[PDB]
Amino acid sequence: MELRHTPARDLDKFIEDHLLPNTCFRTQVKEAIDIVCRFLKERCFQGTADPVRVSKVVKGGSSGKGTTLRGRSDADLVVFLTKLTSFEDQLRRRGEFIQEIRRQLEACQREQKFKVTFEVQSPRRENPRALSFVLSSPQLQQEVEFDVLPAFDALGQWTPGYKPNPEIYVQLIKECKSRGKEGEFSTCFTELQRDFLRNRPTKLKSLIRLVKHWYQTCKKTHGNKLPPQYALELLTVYAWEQGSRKTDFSTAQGFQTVLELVLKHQKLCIFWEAYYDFTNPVVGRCMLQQLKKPRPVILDPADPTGNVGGGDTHSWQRLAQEARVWLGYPCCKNLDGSLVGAWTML
RNA sequence: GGCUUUUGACCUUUAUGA
RNA sequence: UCAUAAAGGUCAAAAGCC
């Protein structure tokens, strides 16, 4: 029943029975999300003496991408505030707004609205990106974990399917590389990150789910010294774009392709021009600098300052060693014993 | 041939915030 | 119009099952 004992033919069956989200489970999470969202915009930042307001609460993480694994009762919310004027503004006052959110959550708890339990000092205080807590509500039938991140609304009103004005990227690059905070404000472009995955073929998302499951399995051996999970998601998308491009493909072949790409990480230089490009001199120069870095280079399609590769070859070494082992498992093999084969790249 | 689910798309509408 | 949840209808993709 485990993935490592599942034959290649049966990968889609494994995904269906173990990875695809459940209806009743998902409805609980969505209601929990609405409860927190309404708390933020109706209670937390709504006082008449309070100038700060919520322009939008954006659902990030896997829930925004539609790549959620079954049994995952959690949500990552980015709350964009009208007060922040810049990225540096966010970097300084984020600890302040997190304190306020926590104080209002305590107030609602005092008023017996719901029950919240905060994560105790897993990160050290200063500088935190998120407020972490578990929500318990009488309306809900299960508990839901939350990560809430206050952010400067860099995109403003952005419509999916369109390129942001590059001037926001110029602003980002200037502020980032002035204080060495490359990739620090990728959360501001959460909407771009989920948009990059939203319209992908259904089976590609299922493959992402499978890759994520494999990743988290390895994560129980190595812990947090692996590359970011987001890097594996981008790598999976890259594999499909270069080697398949079809709604219908072999799940096993896609899986082996990603594993082999992990092995060949020393030659990975991956980027997109989905939301930015070389047309703007400053932006294009930033892109070029990134492509000249030690491999693997996997540039965030939403943030030109972010190399998801991590700049840690040790993490990729540990993942490559898992990749080589898993290539000998039944999940990459036909019943006769031979490998299903990887996609032919370009 | 049929059903269901998951993930998206489109046309309206409701609530809340901007 | 954007964000979060929901209502009605239609469409698509993939998967599972009969």
Image (spheres, coloured by chain):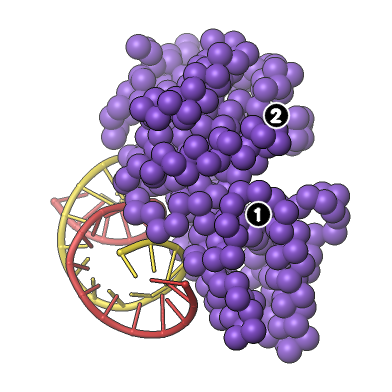
Chain colours: A purple, B red, C yellow
- Mark 2, Cα crowd under 10 Å, few <14 / some 14-19 / many 20+, is many
Q: Position of residue A338 (x, y in %)?
A: 47, 11
Name the element at disc 1: helix
Q: Is residue A317 or residue A107 the one in the foreground?
A: A107
Protein chain holding label 1 = A
Whether callout 1 and callout 2 share a subunit is answered: yes
Question: Left or right: where does residue A231 sit relative to residue A281?
Answer: right
Q: Cβ–Cβ below 8 Å for labels 1 and 2?
A: no
**Residue at 73% from the left image edge and 87% from the top image edge:** A112
Residue wearing tag 1: A89
Name the element at disc 2: loop
Residue A168 in view (yes/no): yes
Q: Inspect the image, locate mark 2, and give the three-letter code of the amino acid beneath it.
A: Leu
Q: Is residue A228 or residue A71 the one in the foreground?
A: A228
Answer above or below: position of A159 versus A307.
below
Mark drawn on residue A305: none
| Sooner in the amino-acid sequence: mark 1 or mark 2 | 1
Q: Position of residue A316 (x, y in %)?
A: 67, 20
Q: Inspect the image, locate mark 1, and give the three-letter code of the amino acid beneath it.
A: Asp
Q: CA distance from mark 1 to mark 2?
A: 31 Å
Q: Position of residue C3 (x, y in %)?
A: 44, 63
Answer above or below: position of A122 versus A205.
below
Q: Position of residue A263 (x, y in %)?
A: 58, 14
Residue wearing tag 2: A226
**Residue at 62% from the left image edge and 13% from the top image edge:** A294
